[PDB]
Image: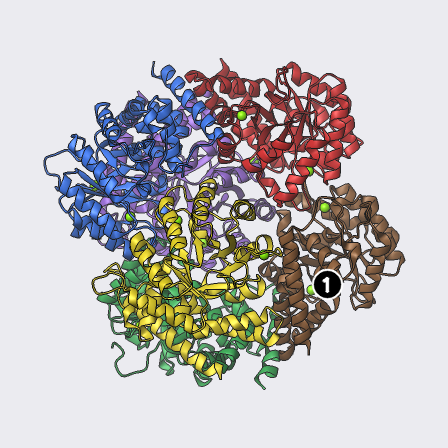
Chain colours: A yellow, B green, C purple, D brown, E red, F blue
């Protein structure tokens, strides 16, 4: 067992953090650290930085690494996102993760060049995995990449890279089932992570997931934790917990579905604003903004969810 | 605000009326008016005539306008359907609607000629909208037409046509979400209408709809109203109402699904017959009829729904 | 044999005529008759009126019948299009065709109401076929209608309706193959008609077609006739004719492809204008018009085709 | 009525039996008979042998017929599966079924040669049906076969073959709806059978099914029977039964979904093993086996279902 | 090199033989041998027996092996088809092939049970390959099987089975390109075989194929050989040969396309009949027959091809 | 007219240059400039740098700008590619293009963040266009981006950005037709560019293209120029040129098709190597390499094309 005696960095409820943007459009790292600390205190187990929720394409590799360092310095368990323009850059994020003392590695597929090519993905994964060989790793899988990591690739990688311990799935319930049935269900150290906000109950109950990366949990941490706890109890055969998890998931479905689309950072930042956190007002691109109707729509759905939850929870 | 002080013609529960057919296959307008009056008295807010439920392709433009006049004369709030073989005919339905004192306009896409062409749809909508500029209007959207009205078109039309106040969606939950997110959720006079019998809870709860056009509500008015009232309460955050709305919707799903297919008039007329309204026995085409198995199937599903509802409702 | 001793109305090259529109937007029937007479004189065998090329949805049933009468009175062999808003109207076009002395009937599927329902299409076809039992008939088949007439339906109809002698196919080469293999290749009176401008060589050579309805042949009658004659010779095993037919078809492909889309009347009218026939300038809907780029594009493709043909033909 | 006074062989809950495999990889018929007897005693109404659950492709026609005979000799009502490499072999299974005294016939489409050809399927069905004209028959319908039996074929067959009394559907809820609406809902002797483990509630409640063939019911007979009884009560309008049926179906969904895929025999045998029936350890092909992860996954889902059911059921 | 000094059994033009059927519907092996001898004498290099062209599903394993033996005894180089109901039966065809002295092995994917499962296909291929380890082998690839052999599988098999020397592709030009680019183009003993009648020019010219299995070449051996010789010359950069190959392929396309569909044996037998070989009149299933229209269609296309070729060839 | 008196930078044949990689994996700019100079001397009109052919994702923004400067300094007309990780970076490429004296701008859609969102693409295009307002610009359109620039967007941009003069299309013949019909065929300064190696004849002849960006033209400049010259002559109605262009295009089709897939840089570099230019041996990622079979396949297709062309060209 790679992590030995310590509880896995890939278990529990883990927010993918947004990167607060100043008026000058540079990242507010004090605010990032504060939010990170707050979310751990609410019951989250770790954070992910800097992933797509954190606006990685819009920040330099150096900005991201400064962020990671600040979060790690502050005592927050960090899983480092390695999304990058090229392999060399992904690799440098992983080197830095190990150097700085991050607790985990999120290994993202190659983009922009040969993205569909399985042999190129294998070499890219291997480059990243061997760059931080002491840091436990998950592979991120998603239909977005034009490519799917299957059992044969996963285990070929794991044969050479013992730090590969998990699989994070973004795609639908069917893709999750495939991963649970064929990759993550041996009696071993390999675990499945839920990787989209809309697949919580399916992941915990039907797929034996042990952890979940959350976008909406930045905004509704207590409520998302409550869902995961119901799901976990349901996964032990608790009938009442299963029924309650399904209702809470249904109520949370609209707001969670923003995670599935291209505007997830715009939608989740604006919800942070509605919760009163005005550091989430601006975007790194000056012209990126929800429209009037989009705003109206989130406002109504956020109001409806909080009203529902207040009623349902007692 | 276009309608000013009066409650919107596009709110509440609105049946699309069927046109009763005599033995000589001409329309029974006394029966249409009687049914209209009855449905308003059951709690419906307005009616639609003459739409696809009313067999518009099978009736002359003149027959339809006689119908509209009778309904309007009788005190029933009428939303006029403008479905037509060509723009000139659609336009004449709209002129007549304004002349006669109808309360609303359902603006249907061009058919048969250039149906997929967005520029032609724009000109057609504009022709209809400006034909009845004093009558509040909704655009009907449906995958049937080979074409989708998007936010950019809707608002370009609205810039020139202030009577355009609503959007009615027939397509799936995804198409409804798009309309709610991008068209109907500004803090303005623009509202979303549910436009298929199977999308009630999603429309009210998830999409902020304010009204619903109903086919099955001709047959089960009290029960469909009950669903809409549960949904409306659910949309305010009532947990118990949400759970009850989902069960009633599930129970009503088979019968409502007849609205989605090509035989909706055959299925809904025959249900009217089973409820005891024998003016709904015949069709305008002599050869149009449910088959023996189709009849058996509606009979069993109608029996099952009424039995279920009697049990569930107390 | 239904037509007995006379050559089939469904053989040869047959234009679907456009309906010239006056400044007052009413049909110019003198111009329609003149064009009809001209096209027969160029080598066409018959005409179709009033089909989708003739703007049927935009004209009243009465306007169409006046047109048909004028063409028939003038000595032009006419195949009557029965496209209509309903069965009763289709039926009245067929009654009128027989009354007036038209030579053939194009039987169009039911639209707008139950269009996908095979049983309803059967009853509609039967209604039309028995309305003009003395007039030889073809069924029009197209993916547009949401429905396909298959061998079993065709032959069930033919068992009761001996005037059904042909099958006209608009869909792709695959749909044509199905019709040739399973419907039209018995040693009988049943023939296949080419029903889209882009399928000439395939229809004659690969599918044993005996006639072709043409849109672009209104504009380029000599050149389309030349293609059909090459194809006919190719269908007898002439190697040189086959090679020449393929080159002419390739050269004609862009211009012919306008037949496949929603703007065919706009594109073919404008080509008539470019050929110098200014009676084809206007459309029945005032707002229907090719855009500036569309015009530029037809102008360039028309120039290129005529230049090519002048060079290629000697 | 073909079966006259006796209750239909196609009603109730009917397992498709697996064929236990010895160490020498020959079938254990004592074990098959014992399991059959046990399942009837648990409340099952009949069995199916030898279908795809019974590994038909892996056993000789003679092995299958020995099995059928043993089950019939033991007093178990048997529906004989006629899946075969060719029509002649299918026919010999049907001759043998009638000879031996089997109570029903499952008529499987032609495979391997002309599988998509409706005319060939008709002749094949007719061959099988007339081979055992005294034995009540159902046609098996499935997207697997590249082909669908529609109402017109079903009833053309039934006109000549009065022993055809039922329709078994494997495909989705939509395919079941089509069969219920158009084939099985006349007031006649014709019934619908549920033919995939995942469509129980839909089949009984929404489609008027009267019987269900089950794979998972070999393993969880009491629990599957409990679902069918809830569904049957729900189909009479019992609101409480409907709600309970939906929860039990949801809980059973993962395990039932193994029926939908290519590994159903591997998954259901291994569950039999986990229930303690070690005669289900081996497969006819030596190399056919669940992987380590697949095993882990069934183990966890089986544990979770039993835990859930123990809690939910009181 | 596995075949050492001898020319590969997988090069040249190779008919998949049909099995002539007597009046008693048993195979006519004298006629099979005679046809085989004739085709070798016309320039074919080998034959395939018993594949789908030979009606394998309709014949017992023993009938097939008798056929193979007769062909081998007569001096004809035979590639044995291993299509079968199960692995054990496929394996026995391969054992028999080696025993009897067949020159090659066509390795067909598992059907009917686990057909889509790559791991099961691997084990099946391995079973067959090791059953006849002295006989050179190709793997048959086709979209029919619900499964594709990719480079990784091919080469994993080849590492353990040195008799695997070729790849036969039935699917489209794209699937052929994949095989040429990734499997068959190393400077090694591994060759690509064309495996559908419609892909000859693409296979030889664009994909570096070295041999072709032919259905229509049973009927038109000289003409198919002529195409392959043009293609082979084209593949060496001969411009004139390339242009001629494309014309002959186009002329042969309709007749060759019968190979792509479910009726290939019906279509190719009937062509054998039209060529005057009346041993090809009947089918193993009494009810399998081309319809009247299908017959008419082949008759016309066969006439047209022979007429064309007589003209084109001088 | 934006470019005034000078010939458009977007006409003629324009290679997208590859970036030669040293043993230390840094770019060889001397070699890039030399190749650029050579290609202009062979008849190319301009070059594109740094696009996807130039490995843009693998090079820093600074490396790219050094390249652009070197090419511009050397007298080569350069169209600058603006593909980038974010808008700010795209913008800096455009600022630099104008500063340095590049002759044109290739405007690439936003990637990685909001790629499918049309409103975000509009703002991105506007940012780039206004960054280099003096430099003539084309928008690159491709299905890759999850998004299509349509006529309405193009012309809305052009209303504010007079330097937008062209449209470059990568997608299929259908997407090219749409652009020719609706965007580029007004009598204005707006031109269509061919943007994939496989669409040359269609672009020039059928779509009125005036220029072509080429990948394979780096390798076969004379032969690609010869195709474009035939196509240009064909576009003036030259019959002989049209026939010759089609044969040369067919011969070049395999090699050109490498442009359509993910390995285009690997395939085109290796062809440069086969032509004897060994500066194209290595890749920026050490592990990126054609496989043995891929190499074999390009070697055979390159040999076949040169042999064919030597024969065909006299
Ligand atoms: Mg990456
Ligand atoms: Mg595990
Ligand atoms: Mg309309
Ligand atoms: Mg609004
Ligand atoms: Mg019609
Ligand atoms: Mg015929
Ligand atoms: Mg069978
Ligand atoms: Mg029945
Ligand atoms: Mg096999
Ligand atoms: Mg090789
Ligand atoms: Mg970009
Ligand atoms: Mg222009």
Image coords of residue C114 (percent x, y): 50, 59
Residue D270 vertical position relative to residue F60 in the rendered view, above or below: below
Q: Is residue B228 left or right of residue D153?
A: left
Q: Is residue F204 left or right of residue A109?
A: left
> Tag 1: Cα neighbours inside 10 Å, few (<14), some, or many (≥20)?
many
Q: Chain of mark 1?
A: D
Taking the spot 88% from the left edge, 61% from the top edge, the residue there is: D75
Q: Residue furthest left?
A: F5
Residue F269 vertical position relative to residue C269 in the rendered view, above or below: above
| Front one among B83 and A181 | A181
Q: Is residue D194 left or right of residue B194?
A: right
Image coords of residue F116 (percent x, y): 34, 54
Image coords of residue A255 (percent x, y): 41, 69
Taking the spot 70% from the left edge, 36% from the top edge, the residue there is: E127
Q: Residue furthest right?
A: D73
| Front one among C60 and B312 | B312
Q: Quadrant of the C terminus of chain B?
A: bottom right
Q: Is residue E295 left or right of residue B59?
A: right
Residue E150 visible somewhere in the drawing: no
| Secondary structure under the numbered disc 1 in the rendered image | helix
| Front one among D19 and C288 | D19
Residue F268 vertical position relative to residue E312 in the rendered view, above or below: below
Taking the spot 37% from the left edge, 70% from the top edge, the residue there is: A37
Image coords of residue E256 (percent x, y): 56, 29
Residue hosting label 1 = D217
Residue A136 visible somewhere in the drawing: yes
When asked about the image quadrant of residue E265, the answer is top right
Q: Quadrant of the N terminus of chain B?
A: bottom left
| Front one among A142 and F261 | A142
């Amino acid at each position: 067992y790679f992590q030995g005696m310590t509880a896995s960095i890939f278990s529990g409820v883990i927010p993918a953090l947004m990167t607060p943007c100043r008026q000058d459009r540079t990242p507010d790292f004090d605010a990032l650290v504060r939010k990170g600390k707050e979310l751990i205190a609410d019951g989250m187990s770790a954070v992910v930085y800097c992933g797509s929720m954190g606006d990685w394409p819009l920040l330099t590799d150096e900005q991201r690494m400064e962020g990671v360092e600040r979060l790690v310095k502050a005592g927050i368990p960090v899983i480092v996102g390695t999304g990058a323009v090229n392999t060399a850059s992904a690799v440098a994020h992983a080197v830095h993760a190990q150097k700085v003392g991050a607790k985990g590695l999120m290994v993202i597929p190659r983009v922009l060049s040969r993205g569909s090519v399985i042999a190129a993905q294998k070499a890219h994964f291997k480059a990243i995995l061997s760059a931080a060989p002491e840091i436990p790793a998950v592979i991120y899988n998603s239909p977005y990449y034009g490519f799917a990591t299957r059992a044969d690739l996963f285990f070929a990688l794991r044969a050479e890279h013992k730090n590969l311990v998990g699989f994070k799935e973004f795609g639908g319930p069917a893709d999750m089932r495939y991963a649970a049935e064929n990759i993550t269900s041996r009696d071993d150290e390999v675990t499945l992570m839920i990787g989209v906000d809309t697949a919580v109950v399916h992941g915990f109950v039907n797929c034996g997931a042990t952890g979940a990366i959350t976008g909406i949990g930045n905004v509704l941490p207590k409520e998302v934790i409550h869902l995961c706890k119901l799901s976990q109890a349901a996964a032990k055969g608790d009938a009442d917990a299963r029924a309650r998890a399904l209702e809470l998931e249904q109520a949370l479905a609209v707001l969670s579905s923003f995670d599935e689309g291209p505007d997830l950072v715009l939608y989740f930042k604006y919800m942070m604003v509605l919760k009163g956190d005005k550091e989430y007002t601006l975007h790194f691109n000056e012209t990126d903004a929800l429209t009037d109707s989009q705003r109206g729509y989130v406002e109504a759905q956020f109001k409806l969810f909080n009203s529902w939850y207040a009623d349902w929870s007692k």
